[PDB]
Image (spheres, rainbow, N blue to C red):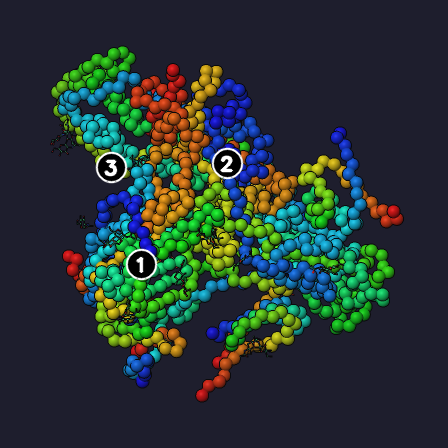
Amino acid sequence: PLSETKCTLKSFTVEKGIYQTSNFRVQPTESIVRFPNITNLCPFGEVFNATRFASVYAWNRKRISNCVADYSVLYNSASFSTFKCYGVSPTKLNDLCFTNVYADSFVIRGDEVRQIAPGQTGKIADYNYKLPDDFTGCVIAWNSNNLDSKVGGNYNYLYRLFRKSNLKPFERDISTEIYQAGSTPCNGVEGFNCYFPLQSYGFQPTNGVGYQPYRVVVLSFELLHAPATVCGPKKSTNLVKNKCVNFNFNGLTGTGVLTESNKKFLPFQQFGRDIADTTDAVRDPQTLEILDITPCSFGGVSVITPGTNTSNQVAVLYQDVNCTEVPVAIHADQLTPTWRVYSTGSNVFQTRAGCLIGAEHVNNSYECDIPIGAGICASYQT
Amino acid sequence: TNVYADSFVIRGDEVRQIAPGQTGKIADYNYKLPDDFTGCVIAWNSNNL
Amino acid sequence: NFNFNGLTGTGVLTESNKKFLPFQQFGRDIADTTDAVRDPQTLEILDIT
Amino acid sequence: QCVNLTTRTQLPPAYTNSFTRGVYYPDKVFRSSVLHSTQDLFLPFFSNVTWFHAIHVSGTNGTKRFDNPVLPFNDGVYFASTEKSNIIRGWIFGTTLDSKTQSLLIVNNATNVVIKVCEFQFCNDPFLGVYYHKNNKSWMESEFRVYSSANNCTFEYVSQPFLMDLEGKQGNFKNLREFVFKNIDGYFKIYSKHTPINLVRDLPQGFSALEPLVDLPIGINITRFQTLLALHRSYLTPGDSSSGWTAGAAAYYVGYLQPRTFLLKYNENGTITDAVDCALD
Amino acid sequence: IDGYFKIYSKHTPINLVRDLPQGFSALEPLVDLPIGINITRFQTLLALH
Amino acid sequence: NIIRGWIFGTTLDSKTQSLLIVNNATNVVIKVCEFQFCNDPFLGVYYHK
Amino acid sequence: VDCTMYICGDSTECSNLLLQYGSFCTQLNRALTGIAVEQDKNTQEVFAQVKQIYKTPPIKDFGGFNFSQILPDPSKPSKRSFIEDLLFNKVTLADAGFIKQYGDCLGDIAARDLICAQKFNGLTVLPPLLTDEMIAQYTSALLAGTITSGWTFGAGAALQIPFAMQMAYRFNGIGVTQNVLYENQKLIANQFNSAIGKIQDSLSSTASALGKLQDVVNQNAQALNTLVKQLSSNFGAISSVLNDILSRLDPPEAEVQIDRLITGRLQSLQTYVTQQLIRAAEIRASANLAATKM
Amino acid sequence: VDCTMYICGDSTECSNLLLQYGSFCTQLNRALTGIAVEQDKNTQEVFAQ
Amino acid sequence: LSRLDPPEAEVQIDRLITGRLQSLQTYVTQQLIRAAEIRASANLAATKM
Ligand SMILES: *[C@@H]1O[C@H](CO[C@@H]2O[C@@H](C)[C@@H](O)[C@@H](O)[C@@H]2O)[C@@H](O[C@@H]2O[C@H](CO)[C@@H](O[C@@H]3O[C@H](CO)[C@@H](O)[C@H](O)[C@@H]3O)[C@H](O)[C@H]2NC(C)=O)[C@H](O)[C@H]1NC(C)=O
Ligand SMILES: *[C@@H]1O[C@H](CO[C@@H]2O[C@@H](C)[C@@H](O)[C@@H](O)[C@@H]2O)[C@@H](O[C@@H]2O[C@H](CO)[C@@H](O)[C@H](O)[C@H]2NC(C)=O)[C@H](O)[C@H]1NC(C)=O
Ligand SMILES: *[C@@H]1O[C@H](CO)[C@@H](O[C@@H]2O[C@H](CO)[C@@H](O)[C@H](O)[C@H]2NC(C)=O)[C@H](O)[C@H]1NC(C)=O
Ligand SMILES: *[C@@H]1O[C@H](CO)[C@@H](O[C@@H]2O[C@H](CO)[C@@H](O)[C@H](O)[C@H]2NC(C)=O)[C@H](O)[C@H]1NC(C)=O
Ligand SMILES: *[C@@H]1O[C@H](CO)[C@@H](O[C@@H]2O[C@H](CO)[C@@H](O)[C@H](O)[C@H]2NC(C)=O)[C@H](O)[C@H]1NC(C)=O
Ligand SMILES: *[C@@H]1O[C@H](CO)[C@@H](O[C@@H]2O[C@H](CO)[C@@H](O)[C@H](O)[C@H]2NC(C)=O)[C@H](O)[C@H]1NC(C)=O
Ligand SMILES: *[C@@H]1O[C@H](CO)[C@@H](O[C@@H]2O[C@H](CO)[C@@H](O)[C@H](O)[C@H]2NC(C)=O)[C@H](O)[C@H]1NC(C)=O
Ligand SMILES: *[C@@H]1O[C@H](CO)[C@@H](O[C@@H]2O[C@H](CO)[C@@H](O)[C@H](O)[C@H]2NC(C)=O)[C@H](O)[C@H]1NC(C)=O
Ligand SMILES: *[C@@H]1O[C@H](CO)[C@@H](O[C@@H]2O[C@H](CO)[C@@H](O)[C@H](O)[C@H]2NC(C)=O)[C@H](O)[C@H]1NC(C)=O
Ligand SMILES: *[C@@H]1O[C@H](CO)[C@@H](O[C@@H]2O[C@H](CO)[C@@H](O)[C@H](O)[C@H]2NC(C)=O)[C@H](O)[C@H]1NC(C)=O
Ligand SMILES: *[C@@H]1O[C@H](CO)[C@@H](O[C@@H]2O[C@H](CO)[C@@H](O)[C@H](O)[C@H]2NC(C)=O)[C@H](O)[C@H]1NC(C)=O
Ligand SMILES: *[C@@H]1O[C@H](CO)[C@@H](O)[C@H](O)[C@H]1NC(C)=O
Ligand SMILES: *[C@@H]1O[C@H](CO)[C@@H](O)[C@H](O)[C@H]1NC(C)=O
């Protein structure tokens, strides 16, 4: 505490007085990792080794649940030229759980890959497939030029060229109502100013790169605000109560002291929030117990200092510690804890201002110097 | 100053994994740049060599 | 006319809103006359008027 | 096999105010929106309850006490307890609580509930207990020293497997377990209610009625009974089987039933919400 | 909204005769249906006796 | 149990896909199809005597 | 204020980034310290005016006058007068003379208890140097001083003066002849004794007069509660919670989000300190007048 | 001060974004109100003696 | 709002909102300082009255 005062004041010398210091803090000693009881691996094969992809015209949406998102399983044989995540840094994927997870699946032309991103325009972005402005997922794409290609052209892949308006995010429209143009009434018949709304792709194996077919997978998911049925490969540990710990609960990290709670979460609520929107309770993913999370740091400390040009001894006042040696129960497993002080010395004095450690106490009274508080002062004497 | 050049051959789809902050088998197991990388990266298609 | 698990009587059976505890088969009114029963096959509560 | 615990500090009994506790539903009848007059053996209102304060593990001059005395049954027993860690686990009901006659043993042990009526040779200082710690943080139960032997067993009941929470806790009491035990005409009738609490020192003031729970067809003479508590043992408290133990975080109360008449108030859903002890004043 | 048809609900006992009861409660999330369609109008389906 | 379902959509006609939600006897079915809807759709219960 | 805890409570990455806004965190602390020093000086200037602490005389014969509800009641554990107990009982403080222990917040209660919630966000309250008992001793001394010597208890050695004479001199001061006091001594004493009882009864009945003191207390409480509520603001960030930022983002992205929250939290603290300084100037002015009037 | 109008006068998108630091907008007005109240008291103390 | 899509516009709007709030905070602070001075003047004037 004296050095802390010296650092604060940018000085090697501290004048006699009272200085405030940082709150008393303790460090966490172990980490608790908890994930839901998921035993299965996610259907990476079905998603990336599919016999067929939908045309962009009428894209598919697969729901994903009760599995491990171990993305590394694709490292042995998949190769993706295109990759971009929007709602999360990709380096964090293995420490997170994912929820409300869906995989959109379709085929587009290579020059159209750039139109998938949110905020883009063009015939695909406007008429076939669109992501929202605030998309929170990640996009994967690759050059399937030996799967989706045919010598005479692959005409099983279709896209919409005409619509009277643009699509909203995640919409599909499979209507074949003939497109009318030029205020020229049309009774469903292709002709002047009347078009079938759909067109096919070529995708011959002999075309240049911009014309090769590409497979696009869009992973749409949410993080940290709901129970998850899909999670990364990180292994869990046992949970320790009434200790200062580090933790990871379904991707939500932090530190603090976990205590049992009496809060009653609804069946769909995984996490709670306090009055200033900070998580203060969680529902454990393996057993649905509710635990309150209390910060490790607390209280306050101040230091009673004689001039440092006289003595390097100081006395320390603890704002949240009584120091009265009240008899307590013996926990069977735990040993009775100590006072939240940096050190307990030879002189412990208890007052209304908090307990003071290191100053001798006398029953005398005098003129105030180096005021401590609540009727108490101190001085340096032989 | 303190100038070094790192040099290697990878697959073209993996070029994107060189940038710091990326993941993938190269970014995770073969070669990685730091979060605060202060340098510059150059790459090209040596398809005839 | 009726017989509910041996308890006989006559009257008009209407659906009720009384909530019997899991162990209560029959109820009683203010002058100790049965005025509701729990049906033995489906646990519906019927008032007897 | 059993052992006498020899480290207990000798402390006096405490007494408390029963207030309005010990009320139960008089029959299996649905009643509502009515006041009803009945007669039965009930804990009298504002009665003298013996307080078996039993958490004395604290202090340098330790007061460790594991209080499991034999108490009279009289006309029926009001029993209640407050606990935070599943310590109060059972009872012995009988004549002399000895091998000479049959008696009733009810124990909630880890993973099951067993009720037997046997000629048990009971321990003078019976107990249950949990010991394992250190290699892993799970607590494990292994001690059962209630009786050394038993024979001529009848009414053997075993419940279904379950898991039990053994870990000791700090903080307030969490579980109020209220019971009424009666021995009438061949039946041992037990009524009960489990209510959440957050108290620190004594039986909470308040009112509820207990539900019928069970009727046990056991034809025995119950004159006295004994409360069965579990011990906390660990690496932290060395000693042999008579000394290497601590008291856990639980305590209990005993009152007695007397014939009384009551006015009971049933609300619109048939819940007893209040009562008048007609002989109180 | 944005590809989802969100439905919230609550089921409450009533004993009214003529109109929507006055009172307050909040509905629970129930379900999120991932249906990418344009809903502009709707129709209520009733059964006949 | 008369109010059993809803139709949600564009024109509520066969030209486009729309959402049909119905609570029918014994089950609940939700489908999104190019339905050719009735102008006066209904469900119903008949048998008696 | 623990200016680190308010911003980066229990967060390592935030804590290191926050080191850059260094002398500023310290500057806020200096400003609050200066206020705290003045609050004790103000108390001392108003009450600790005379270092001679006089005991209430054993003689209560101050002419026909009573004064017992003004003077300290020796039968109480307190050193307060009857009127003072009412003043103290009517103003509501969140608490007083008590220290909350860390273990007291290890429960659900931490989220309901504003004192606990403020402490966990680095906001603390310092105890006064002078206690109620010491103040009671100062008012006791002043009363003993003025009841016996009156004007002369100050500006020199105290001189005892008969109470009737003290008032005769006070009347001469106003310009009322001394003859009035002696001729009407019983009237004056009866009017006074009645007036004091009326004040005491008025105080027992209506506490609204104390609203000024209640407001000082409420205003500081509100300012601290505001600092806690403001923690929820995003300030351009994705989320106001550091843990959400740290969980989803890598360092270089997390840093942007963190800087946005640090700036916002700093604005909240700077605003707080400024308001406390303005309020401090106003309380000093009141205290200076109070000291002057004493 | 109408602290919303000053920032997002007649602008919906701005207004919604402005709701996040909402307590602040309120506190600015509270401070101004305190001044405004004191101004009438000052007049009263000087003249209404 | 005219030239930018929402997520880009949000950056630009946040800069202006922060800016405008800082301006208002400055205003309020100055008014509070001036208010202290006017009160002092009023108190002196009241004393002289
Ligand atoms: C917060 O919740 C508690 C506990 O209630 C239980 O948990 C909730 C989350 C819900 O799921 C509840 O449906 C569930 O019961 C509430 O405490 C309880 O309140 C009820 C009254 O609503 C009390 O009932 C009384 O019981 C006495 C004795 O029988 C009667 O005389 C009374 O007339 C009345 O029926 C009940 O005892 C009480 N529980 C405990 C342990 O004290 C709490 O009120 C609720 N808070 C709020 C703001 O709603
Ligand atoms: C500091 O400790 C004293 C000592 O009392 C004991 O420890 C307390 C924390 C509390 O647990 C007491 O019950 C213990 O006896 C406290 O003084 C006590 O104050 C309480 C409340 O008024 C009173 O019930 C006790 O009898 C007092 N005990 C004695 C012997 O003085 C004091 O309040 C504590 N200060 C704090 C926590 O701020
Ligand atoms: C996707 O399909 C490829 C095959 O095209 C799978 O890769 C093969 O995996 C087996 C082991 O099961 C190896 O023996 C083969 O040598 C691999 N083939 C190639 C070309 O590398 C791949 O595992 C499938 N991916 C998923 C997620 O199911
Ligand atoms: C959702 O359906 C509505 C109703 O049909 C569409 O709005 C109409 O669009 C046609 C052109 O296709 C116009 O001629 C009408 O005047 C529009 N009506 C109204 C009330 O605006 C709307 O465009 C559809 N949305 C999407 C994304 O397709
Ligand atoms: C606890 O101590 C008591 C004595 O205070 C023991 O009681 C005696 O036990 C012996 C057998 O060892 C009998 O022969 C005596 O007749 C018993 N005396 C009485 C008065 O009962 C008791 O057995 C001890 N229990 C344990 C578990 O050690
Ligand atoms: C708790 O009591 C049960 C029931 O008495 C114990 O389980 C029995 O163990 C015996 C061993 O001889 C078996 O023959 C029974 O079939 C078991 N019963 C059941 C229902 O499984 C159980 O071991 C006791 N708990 C502890 C911790 O010892
Ligand atoms: C925790 O560790 C203890 C100690 O090794 C395990 O309990 C032992 O189990 C063996 C049988 O495998 C018994 O022979 C020992 O007597 C037991 N120990 C004690 C002190 O009684 C316990 O099973 C482990 N628990 C978990 C969850 O791993
Ligand atoms: C209760 O158990 C005892 C055993 O402790 C029974 O005693 C029997 O006594 C006869 C005497 O002729 C012996 O031949 C038997 O072998 C004994 N039985 C056993 C199991 O040892 C006694 O009969 C039993 N009483 C009842 C009612 O069951
Ligand atoms: C209520 O709807 C269900 C579901 O559509 C009907 O049951 C289905 O009947 C078809 C007949 O072709 C079967 O192929 C399906 O397998 C059945 N589904 C299920 C879940 O059983 C049911 O018959 C309808 N109710 C009534 C009264 O007609
Ligand atoms: C001052 O007035 C008080 C009453 O306000 C007088 O003391 C009371 O004396 C009666 C005697 O019957 C007691 O019952 C009251 O309890 C006393 N009250 C208090 C507050 O002490 C007191 O004697 C008067 N003193 C002088 C000097 O006139
Ligand atoms: C001045 O007025 C007061 C009343 O305000 C007079 O005192 C009261 O006289 C009545 C006469 O009936 C008594 O009952 C009251 O007890 C008296 N009050 C007090 C406090 O003594 C007083 O006499 C008048 N004085 C002069 C000079 O006219
Ligand atoms: C799921 O529970 C079983 C016990 O039934 C346990 O053995 C397994 O390790 C748990 N699961 C996971 C996915 O970690
Ligand atoms: C119960 O009776 C005993 C008799 O020794 C007495 O000391 C105690 O105070 C009584 N307690 C109550 C709560 O009435």
The answer for how far apart the CA atoms under marks 3 and 1 are is: 68 Å
The mark closer to the camera, 2 or 3, is 2
Q: Quadrant of residue A341?
A: top left
Q: Amino acid at mark 3?
A: Ser
Q: Is residue A95 above or below residue G91?
A: below
Q: Is residue H39 left or right of residue F41?
A: left
Quadrant (top left, top right, bottom left, bottom right) of the C terminus of chain A: top left
Residue F36 or A217: which is nearer the viewer?
A217
Q: Amino acid at mark 1?
A: Tyr
Q: Is residue A243 above or below residue F9?
A: above
Q: Please state the horizontal and vertical placement of residue A263, each as a whole percent of the image.
A: 43, 52
Q: Please state the horizontal and vertical placement of residue G65, each as a whole percent of the image.
A: 16, 25
The tally of labels here is 3
Q: Please state the horizontal and vertical placement of residue G293, each as a whole percent of the image.
A: 32, 22
User: Label 2: few (<14), some or many (≥20) within 10 Å?
Assistant: many
Identify the disc placed on residue A218.
none
Q: Which residue is mark 1?
A: D147
Circle 3 sits in a helix, a strand or a loop, which is it? helix
Instruction: Identify the residue shown where x is 73% and y is 65%.
Output: A52
Q: Which residue is mark 2?
A: G5
Q: Please state the horizontal and vertical placement of residue C35, each as a whole percent of the image.
A: 29, 75
> Which sits earlier in the primary sequence, circle 2 or circle 3?
2
Q: Amino acid at mark 2?
A: Met
Q: Chain of mark 1?
A: D
Farthest residue to the right: give it.
B48
Q: Which residue is mark 3?
A: G204
Q: Quadrant of residue D76?
A: bottom left
Circle 1 sits in a helix, a strand or a loop, which is it? strand
- Whether the residues at callouts 3 and 1 have beta carbons within 8 Å, the answer is no
Q: Is residue I17 above or below residue A262?
A: above
The mark closer to the camera, 3 or 1, is 1
Please indicate, yes or no, whether residue D41 appears anywhere in the rendered image.
Answer: yes
